[PDB]
Amino acid sequence: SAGFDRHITIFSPEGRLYQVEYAFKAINQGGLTSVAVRGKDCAVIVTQKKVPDKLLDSSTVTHLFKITENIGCVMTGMTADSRSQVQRARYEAANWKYKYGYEIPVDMLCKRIADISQVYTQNAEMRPLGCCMILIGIDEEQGPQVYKCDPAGYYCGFKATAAGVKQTESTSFLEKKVKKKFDWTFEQTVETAITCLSTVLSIDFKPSEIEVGVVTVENPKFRILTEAEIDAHLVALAERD
Amino acid sequence: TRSEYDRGVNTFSPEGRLFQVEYAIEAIKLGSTAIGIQTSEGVCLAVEKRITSPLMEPSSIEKIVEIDAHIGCAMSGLIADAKTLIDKARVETQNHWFTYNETMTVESVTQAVSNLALQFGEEDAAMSRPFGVALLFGGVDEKGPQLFHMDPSGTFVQCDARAIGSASEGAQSSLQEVYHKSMTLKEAIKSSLIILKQVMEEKLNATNIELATVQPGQNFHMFTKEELEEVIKDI
Amino acid sequence: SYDRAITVFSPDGHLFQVEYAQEAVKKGSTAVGVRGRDIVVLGVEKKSVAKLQDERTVRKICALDDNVCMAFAGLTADARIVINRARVECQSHRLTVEDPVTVEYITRYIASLKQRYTQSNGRRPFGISALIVGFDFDGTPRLYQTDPSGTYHAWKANAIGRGAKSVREFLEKNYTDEAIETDDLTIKLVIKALLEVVQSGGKNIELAVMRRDQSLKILNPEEIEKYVAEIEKEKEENE
Amino acid sequence: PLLHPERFVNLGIEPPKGVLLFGGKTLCARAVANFIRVI
Amino acid sequence: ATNRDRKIEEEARARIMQIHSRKMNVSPDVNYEELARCTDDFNGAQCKAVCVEAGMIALRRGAEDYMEGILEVQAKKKANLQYYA
Amino acid sequence: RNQYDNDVTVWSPQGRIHQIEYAMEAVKQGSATVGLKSKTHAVLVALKRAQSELAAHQKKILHVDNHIGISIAGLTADARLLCNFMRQECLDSRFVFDRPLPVSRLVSLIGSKTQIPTQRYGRRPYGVGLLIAGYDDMGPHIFQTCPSANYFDCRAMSIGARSQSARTYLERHMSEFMECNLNELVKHGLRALRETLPAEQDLTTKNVSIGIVGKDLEFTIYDDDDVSPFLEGLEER
Amino acid sequence: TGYDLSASTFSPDGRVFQVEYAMKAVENSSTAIGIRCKDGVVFGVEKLVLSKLYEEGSNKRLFNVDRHVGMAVAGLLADARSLADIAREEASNFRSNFGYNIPLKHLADRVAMYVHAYTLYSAVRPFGCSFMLGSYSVNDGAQLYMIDPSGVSYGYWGCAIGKARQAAKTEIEKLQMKEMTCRDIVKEVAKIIYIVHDEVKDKAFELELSWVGELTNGRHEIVPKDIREEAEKYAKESLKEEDE
Ligand SMILES: Nc1ncnc2c1ncn2[C@@H]1O[C@H](COP(=O)(O)OP(=O)(O)OP(=O)(O)O)[C@@H](O)[C@H]1O
């Protein structure tokens, strides 16, 4: 049962889409990693940064994008596919706002992206672009929301999650943390995410080798934390641990 | 190794060759032999008709056909491709007459037929393989009598005397030996019929050949049984 | 691997799959056609059917117009499609030009249809052969034969299908102007040529007759019995 | 290089031996000889 | 040495040319630099074939001969096709 | 190989496409042609083939809009298609702008057109090498274009089978160019073609084709007797 | 392998072998470098004249896509020309659509869009060439970006693409680009090209430069003859000094 692997629309005798599985393997190929966590009234995403040179422009190099004025996303996997998916999400959000008159709910945007991915999986026209996309936002009613857009059209909502090479270990640590006092403050959730990254990579982060984005009920605008803010949080949490 | 470079008309082999086009050129051979000869007095076409069995009335094996009142086309290859290209030639000649109110030159009409045959796999025209047929257009125009040979690859070239079909290689040498620039139409007819008798399975007698002539004067003419017998008397 | 593609050439220069379509034609019940002075006749083998099967739904002879008939040998569904399209185009040509279709014109159209279906790669050739027998608008017993490869010729009498070779040889031997001098000798020749393949002679024979400016007539089984009796009497007398 | 192979050494080229008749092989070789028969 | 721990993966072609033409009557005017220029990756085996065919042109055609030899190593019989190429 | 050269859309595991190379090899399957230019003239000289002594020689130089001509080396089909495209483009340029089309822009358009098939599996690459000799306000231009959609601006170039000898001759004699009359220019080209030809044969009025363009001189083609003034004065080896 | 054919099939590892082969192909051509000085950007390329028959300026690998953007290519020159045409056409659309000059970051994003669209499908092959966009403007400073067959648009202070990219990057790293001016960064670029060029293998060689900066009024253009001559003279002198 080996020939059922070179096409996306061929079912294996056991009923498996080896091409979509390989797409997930490609998700676990960018090397980088990212984590998202939602607190009582805020959500925060933090992703490993890799700029192995003084020549690269860290300003342009990034993996966080504001899909709209109130929704942010972190990419992982192939960078070209990541940017393409980000632009598609931006277009979908703008189209939603134009058509219906109110900003796209995060779950809605995630669902539309999932539908596009499923269409690509079903119709043998394109390969399923291998990027995993995590959205964070503030819903006026349900509070913070965090979602995933894996390259198979599955879009379950989360309390906290991680994507990339070390997603399993990050998930284990995050479930350990969340099983006790799942309700966290802004500082508490930022600390949980940062310490999850630090322990799972077995290293501590300088302010430059890390990116953080935040959305809060008080300030429901996706904001990228600056070097000063991230360094302040790092030092404060390390001191007070 | 020649099994992956000839699955399509648009695949180049390591020698940089279109093997499918070459294959169609090979297919040209299966047809019966035809000989066209150009002379200052006109052009003569003679074809070995290949009646597979009597009871087939001869007016269905169209190896020589008429293009306008000033050209004749001799065919060797698939009857289907023959019919398609003959229809194209007739339509193009009539269109040119309609537009420019003149008679298309033999070179121009052969060029138009070749232009049709060019489209191999171009997704812009719908044939997908070479037309396995070789044509000889012998006609009369302002440049005097002329004869052109067109092959499936879309290539056309002037030929003061040429032979195509199954007996192509064997007849080309005979034409080369017997050809001197100045002849008469009767001399060309005699030489062509002699070559046909040389390279024909059957005994050359009345039927089993067709003979046509285009002269600076009377239009394209098909020699009937009477004239065929008259010439065969003293080929 | 020089096969299984309508648009691929072989070293000898063959289109093997249209050749295979012709071979598929060769696996059909025999159908003979002959032309007379003022009568054109088509005979066809029946092959008989199980008693539980109705007969009016099985057709090997079909009138394409008032002055043109078509005998068939090959795949039945392809036969139905080709005959339907041929009738459609006969009427369309009558519309376009106010003159009944000529046998040569209609057979050329059928040949063009088959050629169109065999040019491309996403189409299967019409695995059939047809005999078109008719009377031109000037009056002439024309008979043409069309093959799956889109090639059509004109004959005086030919047989297609299983017994094509043997029946063609018999017609070759016993076809003559005196043998077609009148409008009954042609029918006698047709039954004679079909008897080398059919068994009963009357229970496995269907004849269609076209007379100048007269509609097609399918001969009755009793008439076929009378004719075969006449041929048997002639044979025994000549013995 | 049967009647005048010394031309090769005259021109400074070494006349070699060993030719592969890969492919009327038998009678063509016999005519070329026109002898060492082998089984 | 194979074809599938410490593995090992113009000027050289010219040198090979002179080495294999050493036992010949090569004329000094020959531009082996030009010969190596007109190579297009032809390896040492092709250089050996070129020299061997130069010797064969000495045999037949008497002996430009180096250009013809390298072309015939390329095997440019060219079998002129009916279609232009 | 054997699984990376079955179509132009697949990369071999070496950073190379094999169908493009196959086309660039097919270009060398045709008869020799060469081109060059002076400070005031552009010229092409080519060896028109003869399929047989009876059949006349197939035409070689194609007459693009009067200020441009081309010499082809490759499939007749692709050569005709490209010639028709050139003629249509030049006619459109003359129709929209009341002045001739620049040769540089013409060759750029040809390069893009030949490049597009080299990416999508919908047709094979255009198997022809083109020597475009044109005259614009800037001056005479000789361009080469290959099936791989690469086009060069060449001062004196050769293409087709056995082009190395002509290229070497042009390399040696390039110093002469830019200060030669038209007769000397055609003599240079004819000598290059003689060198590329094998020794035992020669150039005859029957089998040689010449094309010239330049100042106040629309593209002119000489063949058969027309080339006699050049060959007659041409020196012998 | 089996999964390398076509660019629409993932290998079991999750790698698009067609795009990897495109990267390999681009890392086989002549080298190009660019540097973003504090108030401008400079491109240089080591063109390889494959034959002396070619005149000077043939195979121009430093195209200009819209007046303010220069584009230095490396790899398959056919794909390079096609991508240059696409970039010009996108810039023209942007200017028509928005009545103002196209930002280089946005232009690079659009061209990466195009390249990734090509690499996605299975009826087309990935672009077999990389390139670098550069521009300078009063309201945007100096920008430089590098695009590759996969279609990524990381920003850069400087970059090298082609055969010798790692050595060129190593040489570039030891420069004061953030503060140096155009008039000297051009000389440094020429020196770097002459250092990294391989004479014993590539034989022929030509040095092609360009820049866009304030001193050009934010308009890309080729180097003047005298400036290029002085830059290559400085590069030759530096090479001799290193050889000493
Ligand atoms: N060029 C030729 N001249 C003369 N006879 C020839 C020629 N080619 C073939 N023949 C005939 O072929 C036969 C000799 O061929 P031979 O016995 O060598 O077979 P072969 O083709 O080499 O086959 P194989 O090696 O496969 O057994 C004789 O009949 C000879 O007349």
Image (cartoon, coloured by chain):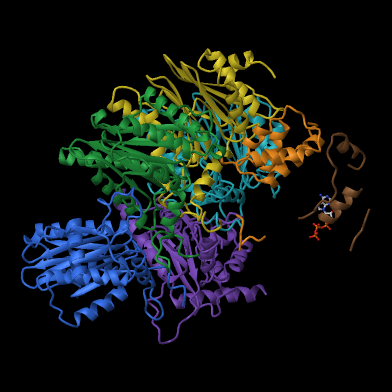
Q: Which quadrant would residue B226 be assigned to in this image?
A: top right
- The quadrant where ligand 1 appears is bottom right
**Split into 4 quadrants, where in the image is the C terminus of chain C?**
bottom right
Q: Which quadrant would residue A32 be assigned to in this image?
A: bottom left
**Residue B93 in sight in this render:** no
Judge left or right: residue C185 versus residue G141: right
Judge left or right: residue G17 versus residue G93: right
Q: Colour of chain D?
A: brown
Picture layout, residue B89 above or below residue F222: below
- Note the chain letter of the purple one: C
- Note the chain letter of the orange one: E
Q: Colour of chain A?
A: blue
Q: Position of residue F101 (x, y in %)?
A: 35, 26
Q: Colour of chain G?
A: green
**Split into 4 quadrants, where in the image is the N terminus of chain C?**
bottom right
Q: Position of residue F209 (x, y in %)?
A: 56, 24
Name the residue nearer the viewer: G238 or G70: G238
Q: Which quadrant would residue A220 be assigned to in this image?
A: bottom left
Judge left or right: residue A150 versus residue F182: left
Picture layout, residue G46 above or below residue D20: above
Determine the residue located farthest toward the bottom in the rendered image. Answer: C52
Q: Colour of chain B?
A: cyan
Q: Position of residue F138 (x, y in %)?
A: 38, 20
Name the residue nearer the viewer: G32 or A130: G32
Picture layout, residue E76 above or below residue A158: above
Q: Residue at x 18, y 82 (%)?
A: A180
Name the residue nearer the viewer: B156 or A87: A87
Q: Colour of chain F?
A: yellow
